[PDB]
Length: 179
Image (tube, rainbow, N blue to C red; front, side, top):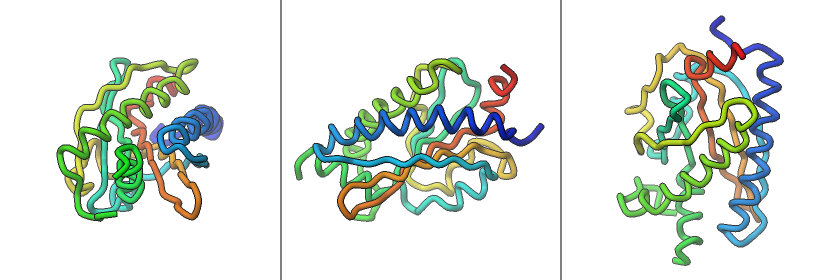
């Protein structure tokens, strides 16, 4: 089938809610302030997701040994620059420099690892960042009409609220969908 079943969605909801809790603790420690995270999932076409991403943005294309194909970890630039500023102790809306992406790549590797830990009992993997892009219109990892599981993490602290989205293409998740 081309779409995710109801029960399969619930499994992914629980997995990513675990991710959400680990992420909250992670970001709270990095930003040294209480950061709340609320997870919500949905399934839609890849086209819909990519068209919703701001230009520019911080798009991390990643994979895992145990997967075949890529997935996307996207972070809004307002969060990206706010996080970086705090970690560095130093937003600009323009696309990030190579230095800024390199510093934030380390943070993303940490967050992807937490994601993998949440996926432990179902399909544990070691994340590998394949590419980093700043323009969503240049990102077409799978066909437009293909369905994708979109995990949205609403990240907030104080009066700031932003997002981190993980896009899991149906084609990538198909085999685990089996067992």
